[PDB]
């Protein structure tokens, strides 16, 4: 149906139907469905004129805000024009000769590594393990590796590797001098998970990637960041990333969003309640295998390869992600965002009529 | 005084004085002083919710708007997160082995080329030529060059190379298979200058860089673009540039700003009237040599090397650009933006008391 690299392709999908992109209910991009944080809307509106000046090239205020939030030194943080920029920055700044990625996973790790000239090795997740990362990867880590990229939780599976396994991997990487890059883009949605930022002080080989776009519903503004405790390496990252890459409005949102308790609480309540109901409902459908995603999306496997769920749902103005373009997966796999109860009901109503 | 790479460092300057950055009158960044275009303010305010979705990864609407403006195919255009991104994109997409830059000039050309591993050759402008680019550069163009970067008009001198000279350079580059990259960031301020976009159809070796930030006062939003008629090379540029690098609000501004006749007319009237008055006034001061800049800034040479005009003016809350960090120039050189009549009068009043 589509040849697009990533979800959120409402313009392309609308063209297939011959309708307006705003008429589609998009389940292919995983953005918090609750609207926009009040802290963000107000800030942008009341300070719009700040676009008349270049942002501070050093982003002192923005980095201090992110640093105070995590209670780490500001020099450990470099904001990017989306976490997507942070991925390209860490790949180019580390300039690995040999790197390992885990498949299926977000396509941009491989693209960034290829652009930097790296030999890429793939650790293949297995359907027999429910697509969860296992300790079998430890033996695959060798001294000649420069970096290992893990996504926690993984895109598209939604699975969070076990904490003791991540700790074992971090320790093995420390011993073998391998940089461990942890993509925590979706970790904000799992309240009881702290991630690895609290453990960076004694682990300069670990790099954490964060995004504010999924959780705070600001993907159009573009804001993410990189965190690491190696003084020299972070200084090099600041030189590698293009000047003024974070726009002024994105910086203003990143300065207030992390303190928006109302939005955070509403988001966790919504996901805990509606997330479980949606997962349960999907699990009942024949021919479907649903993986237990931990954030705001779920990976689905349709038993009947001859049935194109993306095409069938598009007829009902519902856009889902086909995971055929992920190495390791095939056309039987799809990913759907978790949205509002009413929105989820529309998707369920459509799937039930197909299956 | 400062070690900053670029102008607009109001936060750093304010810290030296111990005051608030918004209390400084900044003459170190060259942004249109007229405020913000009405087309832009309205659009951003009435469509703020668009930040809840990723921008169209292909930026079809934005590129069609820029293309209709220049009356060229949309495939010839790639918008960037500031023209600064377009500079890094063209350097990385062309991957030159040998390139020539002209000094003094904007620092990012050299930074982008170094990041791509290029051997950089410098063509030195001369004080004896009033810092204008001359035909002496033609003999310096050799078959082994992959690219030549020219700025039209130049930063920091403000001088526009003669059109017949640019044509001669373009023709020599065509014959020698050299990509000619023309930085037209400031050309919008010179109304009777069309630049080279109208000549790209039969010249696939020419690349034009454009910026909307200086002329439309949106440097905090980040928007520029690259134009070129080589189908294959532009397709490669789209793959080289990071996904979703242009934010949604920047794209909305780029879709309407080029049709803001009221802003354009007010800008040209202001620059023609006030620009000439400011230049004339500066030329009267003893010990100063003022170059005839064609856009919204002027390069100044202070005869007395022992006098730090930047330090002296900062005392009066006026921030200017020291050009000591440009190869080819020394501490006697400074650059000042052309601002409103009242703002310019404050700067003049301060300089007269020093000289």
Image (cartoon, coloured by chain):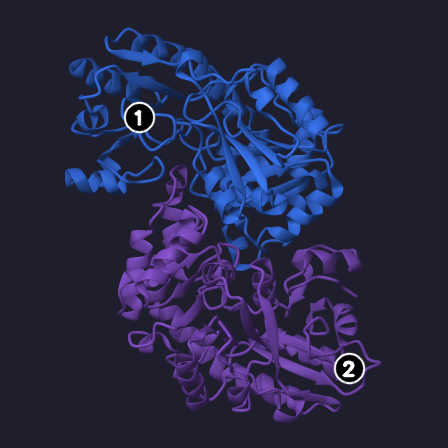
Chain colours: A blue, B purple
* Horizontal arrangement in the rendering, residue A335 relative to residue A12 (left or right): right
The residue at 63%/37% (across/down) is A146
B54 relative to B278, above or below: above
Furthest residue toward right: B306
* Horizontal arrangement in the rendering, residue B47 relative to residue A198 (left or right): left
Q: Are marks 2 and 1 on the same chain?
A: no
Q: Could you tell me which quadrant the C terminus of chain B lies in?
A: bottom right
> Is residue A21 visible to us here?
yes
> Is residue A59 visible to us here?
no
> What chain does mark 2 sit on?
B
Answer with the quarter of the image where residue B12 lies: bottom right
A235 relative to B67, above or below: above
The residue at 74%/45% (across/down) is A232
B83 relative to B193, above or below: above
Residue A222 is tagged as none
B255 relative to A82, above or below: below
Q: Position of residue B230 (x, y in %)?
A: 33, 66
Residue B353 is tagged as 2
């Amino acid at each position: 149906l589509f040849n697009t690299a990533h979800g959120g392709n409402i313009r392309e999908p609308a063209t297939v139907l011959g309708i307006s992109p705003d008429q589609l209910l998009d389940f292919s991009a995983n953005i918090n469905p609750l609207g926009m944080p009040v802290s963000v809307k107000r800030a942008l509106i009341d300070n719009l004129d700040c676009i008349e000046r270049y942002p501070d090239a050093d982003y002192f205020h923005l980095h201090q805000a992110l640093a105070r939030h995590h209670q780490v030194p500001a020099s450990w943080i470099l904001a990017g024009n989306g976490e997507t920029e942070s991925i390209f920055t860490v790949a180019s700044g580390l300039k690995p000769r040999r790197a390992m990625i885990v498949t299926p996973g977000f396509a941009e790790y491989g693209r960034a590594l290829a652009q930097s000239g790296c030999e890429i090795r793939r650790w293949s997740l297995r359907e027999a393990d429910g697509w969860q990362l296992t300790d079998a990867i430890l033996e695959a880590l060798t001294p000649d590796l420069d970096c290992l990229f893990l996504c926690t939780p993984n895109n598209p599976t939604g699975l969070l590797p076990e904490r003791p396994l991540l700790q074992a991997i971090a320790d093995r990487c420390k011993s073998l001098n391998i940089n461990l890059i942890l993509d925590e883009a979706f970790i904000d949605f799992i309240p009881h998970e702290t991630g690895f930022i609290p453990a960076l002080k004694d682990n300069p080989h670990i790099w954490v990637l964060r995004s504010l776009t999924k959780f705070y519903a600001i993907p159009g503004l573009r804001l993410g960041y990189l965190v690491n405790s190696d003084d020299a390496a972070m200084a090099r990252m600041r030189r590698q990333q293009m000047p003024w890459s974070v726009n002024a409005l994105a910086a203003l949102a990143g300065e207030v969003a992390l303190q928006d308790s109302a939005w955070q609480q509403a988001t966790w309540h919504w996901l805990r309640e509606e997330g479980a109901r949606f997962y349960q409902a999907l699990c009942q459908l024949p021919l479907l295998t649903v993986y237990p995603g931990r954030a705001n999306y779920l990976l689905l496997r349709c038993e009947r390869e001859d049935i194109d769920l993306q095409r069938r749902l598009l007829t009902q103005r519902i856009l889902i992600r086909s995971c055929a373009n992920y190495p390791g997966l095939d056309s039987r796999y799809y990913r759907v965002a978790i949205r509002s109860a009413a929105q989820n009901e529309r998707l369920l109503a459509a799937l039930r009529n197909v299956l």
